[PDB]
Length: 43
Length: 43
Image 1 (tube, each protein chain N blue to C red):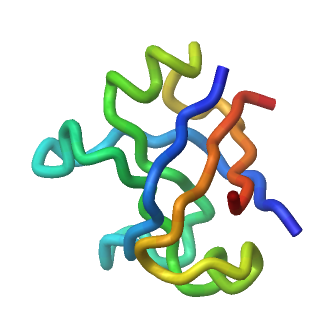
Image 2 (image 1 turned 180 degrees about the vertical axis):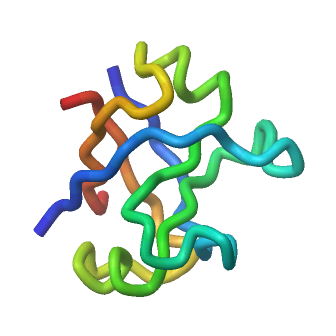
């Protein structure tokens, strides 16, 4: 499965880090673990 | 276009919120604004 989510601004500490933060329930839905590579696209 | 990134844990204020935090570089490359809906797919 893939997951839909709403765009929020990154906290300033995370600037330029090439990450997406997602909580454990959304990671489980996507079947990802921390550090996995995801792809993000406009709907 | 696509933003490819590494999954990281949700910040504690964001647990449950169904959001994906994205810095201005990423949001610009996607062409999305805060509150816009995106799809996250595992690679």
